[PDB]
Every structure is written in C-alpha cells, then in structure tokens.
Image (cartoon, rainbow over all chains, first blue to last red; front, side, top):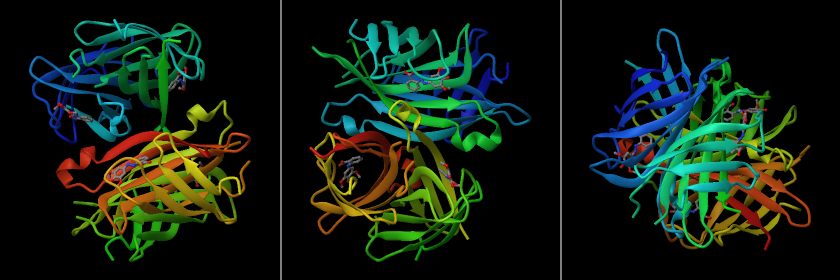
Length: 116
Length: 116
Length: 116
Length: 116
Ligand SMILES: COc1cc(/N=N/c2ccccc2C(=O)O)cc(OC)c1O
Ligand SMILES: COc1cc(/N=N/c2ccccc2C(=O)O)cc(OC)c1O
Ligand SMILES: COc1cc(/N=N/c2ccccc2C(=O)O)cc(OC)c1O
Ligand SMILES: COc1cc(/N=N/c2ccccc2C(=O)O)cc(OC)c1O
C-alpha cells in the first residue's frame, strides 16, 4: 500500500509501481533525462516484512518500442513512510560497451522519490 | 539463450536465470555470504536488442521463507558472450535502517559471474 | 579562493580546506558520524584550470591522535560557485577487513557541502 | 614499505607511491585510458596503525602540463600484504559538468593493483 502509487524524482521522472504481496515490484518508469521517450517496464523486489526503512530495488532496461539506449539502471534504496513518504536511492546505470571501454560503462548517482 | 543458465560469482553464490525474449530476467539467487540461507527470488531487465556488451540488471530482496535480512541488492552490468561468457557487475546493497543510520545503509561492490 | 574556506555537510560535519595554486587540497575534517572525534587530516586534488563545476576529490583516513576506525573515505565531486557555493559529492568509505569480509568493506553515499 | 613502491592495475596504469610514517600517500599516476597523457600527481591518506587489510585512498585530478580532462578520480580500498601484495579498490571519477549534466557526472569502477 505504502509503496504502491506514483512517485517523482528531483529530475522530474515518473515512477509508477505496484508492490505485490510476494515482495514483487512492477510498474513503468518515465525518464526526464537520457536518450528516452515514453515509458519503460520496471521490475524489482522489496522487503514485504520490514522491521527502519523498507529495503527495495528495481531495474529498468532503457529499451521500449520506440528507443534503445543499450543500457540499464538499477535503483537500490529504502522506502520511508510518514506524512511525506520518500524512496531514497542510489543507482547504477551501465551501458553496453566494448571490452576496451568497459572501464567507463557505469554511472553512479542518487535519486529521491516523492509520492504524489 | 546465452544469458539463460546457471552462473557463479567469485564468492560461490549461484545465479539461476531465465532471459525472456521481451527483456525480462527471472530466476533464483543462492548466496555464499551474509545473513542468508537458501534461494531468493530475483527479477531484472536486460537489453533484448543489443548493438558491444549486453546491459542488464536485477534485484534480490534478502527475504525468503527462512530468513529476512531486511536488505536488497541490485546488480548492474553487462553480459559478454563468447567461448568464456561473463557477466561483469557492480552492486549496491541497501539495508533498511532508521533515519540516523541512513548515511551508512548502502554497500557497493563488484561481482564477476561465469558459467564455471 | 572559491574552494578555500569552511564548509558543512547535511550531517553537520565540518570541512576546512585550502586550495593551493598547484591543484592541491589540504585541511582538516570534523565528522558528525562514525567512530570519530576531533579533526582528521585531509588531502586532495582539484582542477586548478576548470572549464561547468570544478572537479575535485579528497581522502580522510579515520586515524588521528585519539582514535583509529581503520577506514578511509574518499569524496569525489565538483565545486559549484555562485551566491550559494556548493560541493556536490559521492563518497566511498572502505574499512580494513579480513579477506572473508572484504565483500562488505565499502559503503557508498553522497554529501552536499555548503560554504560558510 | 609494503605500500611504498610501483603498482599496476588491470588496465596497465602505473601508480608510483610513497607511504609516509604519518599516514600520507604521495606519488604519481600514469593512466592507460582516457583523455590523459603523462603522469599526474596523486595525494592520499592511509591507516598507519592497522589492526586485517589496510584502509587507504587517494585522488588524482586529471590535469598536468599537457592536458586537462576537467575530472578527478578517487580510489578507496585496502592494501593486502603478503607474498602477493594487492591493493583492491573502488573508484569514483567525477567530471566537471554544467548543472544540467550533473546527474551523469560520476563513473564508478574497481581496480586491483599488483606489483607485477
Ligand atoms: C543511457 O541513456 C539513457 C539514460 C537514462 N537515465 N535515466 C536515469 C538513469 C539513472 C538514474 C536516474 C535516471 C532518470 O531518468 O531518472 C534514461 C534513458 O531513457 C531516456 C536513456 O536512454
Ligand atoms: C543484508 O546483508 C546481506 C548481504 C548479503 N550479500 N550478498 C551479496 C551482496 C552483494 C553482492 C553479492 C552478494 C552475494 O551473496 O553473492 C547477503 C544477505 O543474505 C540475507 C544479506 O542479508
Ligand atoms: C568507519 O568509522 C568511521 C566512519 C566515519 N564516517 N564519516 C563519513 C564517511 C563517509 C561520508 C561522510 C562522513 C562524515 O563523517 O561526514 C567517521 C569516523 O570518524 C567519526 C569513523 O571512525
Ligand atoms: C575525465 O575522464 C578521464 C578518465 C580517466 N580514467 N582513468 C581512470 C579512472 C578511474 C580508475 C582508473 C583509471 C586509470 O586510468 O587507471 C583518465 C583520464 O585522463 C585525463 C580522464 O580524462
């Protein structure tokens, strides 16, 4: 219930998610940045029996019917309930690269999600 | 096909994955370290129409029928096919923490998966 | 000039730094969290001829005359001038560990520094 | 003594370091990748009174007499002594960027240094 809903990050990206009773996370992601357009499928897992924030993570491969950025982002964070529910994350964005360029394949950042 | 199979990291953890034609990653993860025992459900996404490496990612919430470590790991990387196929990753392990311990909620590492 | 001064992060930690004409960073760090007390020596490097933020980084080994946490933090970020000068960073905190526990040796986070 | 010497990462970059009794790391870094040429000054800190691995870190701003990549890398890790001494690190490479490209300013990787 807590997790399920629409969330936006500081970049203006949109995350629509449903938390299943089995610890599954499914929804779609709409990105404000990068080489993207439209929504992308997301899938993740969360602690369906948390103690403290709720640990969760999700992935988006930046490929839909319109574009392919040949990359994937994984968000690792925790959900924090209250008046102002937030999802605090750290993410890794890996681009498919040649062996020579593999060293600079992964970006790291942090996103804060606000529930609408 | 290539991604689909049983993989092992340096630590001896086992990742059994099924790669869907649509870009879905589904499977089971069995760890060799941490507050864990047995297999855990994994879910991810991958680039199903790659260009050189194949971008992918997945999440495991460290909760099963036996234990709950109140944490989740996300692996972000690329599959490199060939005679000696590998999955080179970087991971974030976030524990559910109180707001006071939030600064030290996330661990970062790298794992190399092979079929051996 | 820009970089040189007293800065505080969101945790209430204190960073006193002087930027040398040669791209050197020296000062002391006073931590609000962890197993620390008093100041610790810091050393870093910055782009003394920036274009865009100014790229910089610094390290602190958590050892002084009073305590030893057997760990080191490296902050990688950029300085951004203006009315409100800020240092936006990502950090890695590695703890000396045995080979068995090396996998969980490194924490990752992000700090924003405000100049006073 | 142990840390002091010439080390090489997987990429073939060369790290010449001097470890001070007081916990200072000073030296030169010569890269094998990126918008770089020649040696760059490095500065860091290390635990000079370790317990098993030895925590350390260092920074290189990618500016010298020949080029300026307007970026800086920080390596955070541990020195493991013995017959086959190694320095296992994780690094953050931040480029100076405009505020619009700040989200993708930082790369993350891992380097293993040996004396061979
Ligand atoms: C690699 O190239 C691309 C990058 C991209 N980054 N998104 C993100 C990545 C990490 C964290 C947040 C976002 C966020 O959007 O909130 C999005 C793309 O789809 C537009 C794309 O093609
Ligand atoms: C929350 O702290 C925990 C950490 C944990 N590390 N595993 C991993 C973490 C990152 C990358 C690989 C592994 C790997 O095992 O391959 C496993 C746990 O199992 C419950 C656990 O609770
Ligand atoms: C490992 O154990 C310790 C950890 C510690 N984290 N500091 C930090 C680490 C990363 C980022 C910010 C801080 C910050 O303080 O702003 C500080 C210690 O000195 C108190 C200490 O012993
Ligand atoms: C700003 O983008 C750049 C990246 C760059 N990568 N080096 C490294 C980065 C991280 C870890 C190891 C290395 C290593 O070389 O061992 C080197 C540059 O030299 C100017 C440069 O400009």
